[PDB]
Amino acid sequence: GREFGNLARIRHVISYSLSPFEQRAFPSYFSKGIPNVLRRTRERILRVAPPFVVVYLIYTWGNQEFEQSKRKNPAMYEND
Amino acid sequence: KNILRNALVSHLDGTTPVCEDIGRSLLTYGRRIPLAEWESRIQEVDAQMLRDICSKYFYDQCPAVAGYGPIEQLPDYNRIRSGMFWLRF
Ligand SMILES: CCCCCCCCCCCCCCCCCC(=O)OC[C@H](COP(=O)(O)OCCN)OC(=O)CCCCCCCCCCCCCCCCC
Image (tube, rainbow over all chains, first blue to last red; front, side):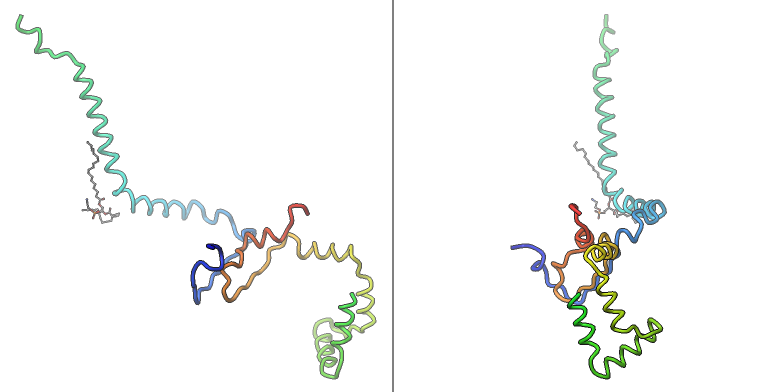
């Protein structure tokens, strides 16, 4: 019922493609991969990173608070 | 071979296609190839050299595809390229 031939109505659209044996599999891989990755990470880093930053701060604070919770209070054994 | 013989002789009928064949033969081959030479080149063709030449020109070759109309179910290039050979030879 839902196969190729009856998916959508498309008019006046031209597509050009070439054979995979005709073109390279890695056309300028590093020289255009690096700026594209940098663009994607600079468009998403402010939405993604600060929650995990404050997870790191909460994790370190909780671990150190537990460590000083196990620490001996020097105020005890001071009266006698 | 019989269909090709009929096609060549029935095409060379009337003054206009004969003049057309003369003009194309002098422009392309540089000479007019007679029908006896065509018949000799037809009768030297057998099944073994036909499948050899067809494997030379059709098997595992990258095709050019041109579609116009409702061509969404026309397969893309990987499926046609994979259909250009058989896994069983
Ligand atoms: C006011 C924004 C100013 C931005 C200045 C930066 C320069 C902007 C212009 C140059 C372009 C730089 C690249 C742009 C990349 C995409 C755009 C972008 O980053 O936009 C800012 C982004 C979205 O802004 P918007 O959603 O409108 O802000 C609502 C804030 N709630 O908003 C952000 O990224 C802000 C995200 C802040 C998130 C704070 C979360 C704090 C709480 C975390 C709790 C986690 C759990 C804690 C523990 C719970 C249990 C104990």
